[PDB]
Image (tube, rainbow over all chains, first blue to last red; front, side, top):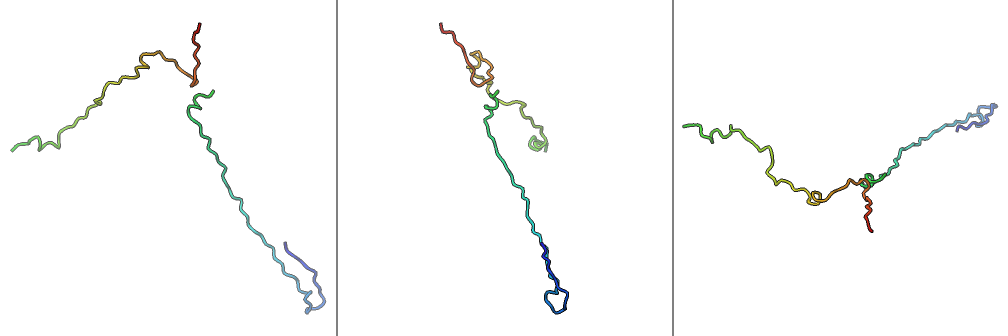
Length: 51
Length: 51
């Protein structure tokens, strides 16, 4: 977030008369795809003989 | 000087038999002799007279 401050208005020489600088910043992050998998093997005769 | 058969060998027609020289097949003596049933389950059941 940016940061502000209180500033004086009395004299040009006072350091408290200078308006403060501030930045804003951002970062990246990634939503990365990943894979769930399984193989279910069975004998053809099991498939043939089951009801 | 004449056209011998060797001189015209490259022009002669060719012929391959349309069938193979093989024994006539027997089939199983068991399948030929014994009566068979269609199975649907892999392990059929068989009641046999006992008394």
